[PDB]
Image (cartoon, rainbow over all chains, first blue to last red; front, side, top):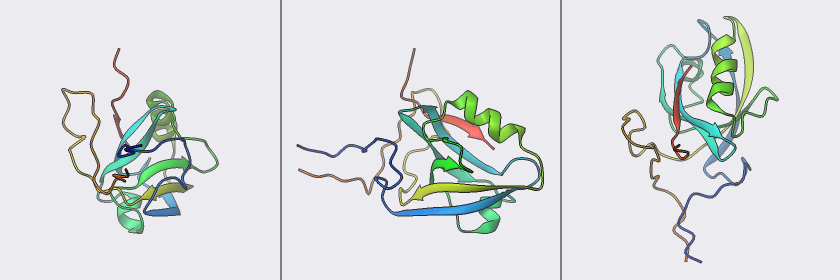
Length: 129
Length: 11
């Protein structure tokens, strides 16, 4: 009862809003979006700001608010920061990836602001009895 | 120590 908390399993499809699979071309080395999360199997990555000149920005079919589920077969679903950053930082200019991401969650509290264990509380969350 | 904190991965 009182399920007013963010649901979790790994399921892209549990995730609400819009589930999209969009290709981001590794442009200018890496991507060009800042993403918060991916700390544990329990914590997924989420876009907190799309960096202008980023392939998300550019492709326009990915926006701040997409939650990063997986990418180019790689199970980045609950990927550890060190691991996810390793992939995302090592990529070359001119490459391609298929982003499996789910958007619909509006960016509420700033995950840009440290000094706290960052758990942003999202609206448009199910406040079910 | 802390677990629930989403990390800034600027890519």
